[PDB]
Image (cartoon, coloured by chain):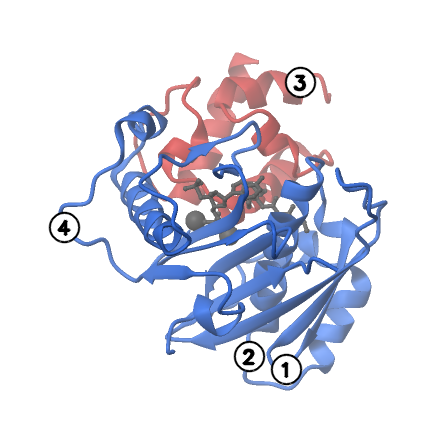
Chain colours: A blue, B red
């Protein structure tokens, strides 16, 4: 499977992705007021990514259902379903799962490119910038660090409903396509478990970085 | 807050790379601002205003007016 998301998450979690905005897509009526005043780019990426999500949802048996946004913008999934969506230029992706098998999932997409000026300093711990320099050349480790941190937050928030700052997570990137997220604050979950470390995966292809984190049922 | 509101609007069009006037009560996500652009904007406000501003405030106050008034209380 040459698909980015399907290559870094288990097959148990159906995923769907698109690299353009196919003509004729539209939002569900309950979703239109969410983008009723947004510009063309924000509208297209919103509609296309939710098409991928609903396609991945029907693999799990879930029929056509609107996907709205919560208080902090998180996607509001049907009861029992946990998912994640991401969209950047040239990519729209979505993955869903049942909480009977996975408790959370997060994915993030970024162009394989150096971060803009000044961003790496505000999102990386001093120990992280040193580790990124020691990594082998040929890979924009700075943005792989940024995108993996967004994935850390996207898996953290649905099990926590609390803020996680860039300074609150220590990410160690391994060149073999894996990475770990070490949470530096107290990770109280709504379940009662403490969340201290995440296991992640990443892939670079077609000028795109894609990071993904799946928590296990334990 | 009105003097700073138009000052954030100048910075927003610099990260958004546009030249259109911005309604001060329209959320910036509807204009195409994403997480990376919000970090860019935050660093440009920290420079222009010379004050340490946390990143979580850009989305706690998702409009220009919501951001401007929250910033003068940081003065
Ligand atoms: O910014 P990215 O495009 O990298 O990810 C965007 C997606 O993250 C998801 N997201 C936003 N806030 C989130 C949060 N607090 N927790 C989890 N996922 C979130 C949204 O689905 C968003 O897509 P939408 O804004 O079209 O709903
Ligand atoms: C490990 C810590 N990293 C994060 N907390 N990252 C985000 O919060 N990113 C983000 C933001 C903040 C700029 C706004 C809207 C949407 C997103 C991504 C869902
Ligand atoms: Mn996006
Ligand atoms: Mn992102």
Q: Position of residue A136 (x, y in %)?
A: 65, 86
Q: Nearer the viewer, mark 2 or mark 3?
A: 2
**Numbered tag placed on residue A175 in the rendering:** 1
Q: Are marks 3 and 4 in contact (CB under 8 Å)?
A: no
Q: Which comes sooner in the sequence, label 1 or label 2?
A: 2
Mark 4 belongs to which subunit? A
Q: Nearer the viewer, mark 1 or mark 2?
A: 1
Q: Nearer the viewer, mark 1 or mark 4?
A: 4
Helix, strand or loop at label 4? It is: loop
Q: Residues within 10 Å of mark 3 (few under 14, many from 20)?
A: few
Residue under label 2, please give it: A139
State the image quarter where residue A47 is shown: top left
Mark pair 2, 3: CA separation: 41 Å
**Same chain shared by disc 1 and disc 3:** no
**Same chain shared by disc 2 and disc 4:** yes
Mark pair 1, 4: CA separation: 38 Å
Q: Are marks 1 and 2 in contact (CB under 8 Å)?
A: yes
**Numbered tag placed on residue B72 in the rendering:** 3
Q: Is residue A92 left or right of residue A213?
A: left
């Amino acid at each position: 499977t040459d698909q980015l998301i399907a290559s870094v998450v288990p097959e148990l979690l159906p995923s769907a992705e698109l690299y353009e905005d196919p003509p004729g897509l539209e939002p569900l009526p309950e979703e239109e007021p969410l983008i009723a005043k947004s510009v063309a780019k924000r509208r297209n990426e919103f509609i296309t990514v939710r098409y991928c999500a609903r396609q991945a949802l029907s693999v799990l048996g879930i029929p056509e259902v609107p996907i709205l946004k919560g208080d902090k913008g998180q996607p509001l999934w049907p009861d029992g379903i946990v998912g994640s969506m991401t969209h950047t230029e040239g990519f729209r992706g979505a993955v869903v799962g049942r909480t009977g098998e996975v408790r959370s999932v997060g994915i993030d997409a970024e162009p394989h490119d150096v971060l803009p000026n000044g961003v790496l300093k505000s999102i990386a711990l001093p120990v992280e910038r040193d580790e990124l320099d020691a990594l082998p050349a040929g890979t924009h480790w700075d943005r792989l660090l940024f995108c993996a941190k967004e994935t850390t937050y996207k898996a953290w928030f649905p099990l926590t409903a609390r803020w996680l700052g860039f300074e609150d997570a220590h990410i160690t990137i391994d060149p073999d396509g894996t990475f770990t997220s070490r949470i530096l604050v107290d990770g109280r979950a709504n379940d009662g478990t403490v969340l201290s470390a995440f296991d992640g995966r990443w892939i670079i292809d077609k000028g795109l970085i894609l990071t993904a984190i799946v928590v296990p049922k334990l | 807050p009105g003097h700073l509101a138009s000052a954030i609007a100048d910075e927003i069009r610099a990260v958004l790379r546009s030249g259109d006037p911005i309604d001060h009560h329209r959320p910036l996500e509807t204009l195409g601002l994403d997480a990376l652009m919000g970090l860019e904007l935050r660093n440009r406000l920290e420079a222009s205003l010379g004050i340490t501003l946390p990143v979580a405030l850009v989305w706690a106050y998702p409009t220009i007016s919501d951001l401007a008034t929250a910033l003068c209380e940081r003065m």
